[PDB]
Every structure is written in C-alpha cells, then in structure tokens.
Amino acid sequence: SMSVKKPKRDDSKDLALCSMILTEMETHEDAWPFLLPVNLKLVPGYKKVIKKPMDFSTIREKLSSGQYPNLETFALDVRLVFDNCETFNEDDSDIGRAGHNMRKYFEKKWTDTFK
Image (cartoon, rainbow, N blue to C red; front, side, top):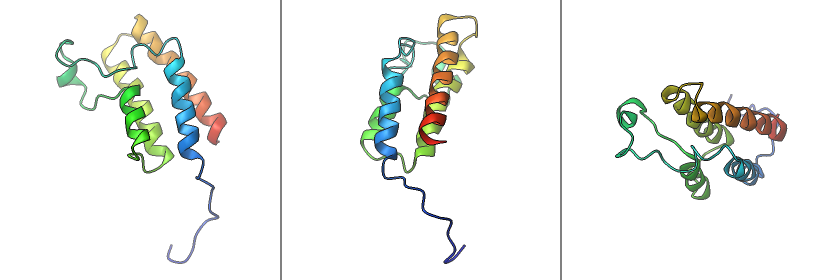
C-alpha cells in the first residue's frame, strides 16, 4: 500500500532474458507453424474465429520496440500463440502436436529462468 512495499525483485535483465527465450523458441524445429502471422486472406475461418492472432515474429517486434511493460505481458502473448493453435487445430495433426510441444518447451524455460 502507500509507503509499504515488498522488497524490489531485480527486473533489469528481464528484457534480455525474454529475448533469449524467444530466440530458443524461434530456432526449435517445431516452430514453423508459429514463425509468421497466419495469412488471413488464405486461411478460411481464421479471421472470424481467432480474435487475437499472435505469432513469434509479432512478439519479436513488440519486444524490440518496448511494447511489453513487464515479463508477464510477454508470457501472455507467447501462451496466446499456443491457445490460438489449440483453438484451430486438431490435437492429432502435425500443427496441433507442434503447439503442444512448443508450449511445453516454453513453460520449462520460463520456470527455469524466472521461478
């Protein structure tokens, strides 16, 4: 509350560390469904169904331009990529499996870097 604060957690490296995580997600062999925005002209149903499209290149541009206020807004966009994937793709599909694999990969890096 006013003039009453928990001890200051050092967040000065968060930007660099989210960049490193994002690099590792970018270079994973199962990243290919997620590297670029879904083409809304060429994929029937996507525009109407997925209210907030997100992809790794969009996260990279947001990260590089100071559009994440803190490390949690960064995690929310990464998770959005996988949530969108599950919304549109069957689990038993190459893309559906890719999304589960990448979500697992991300959540481990996230816990190990920050928790």
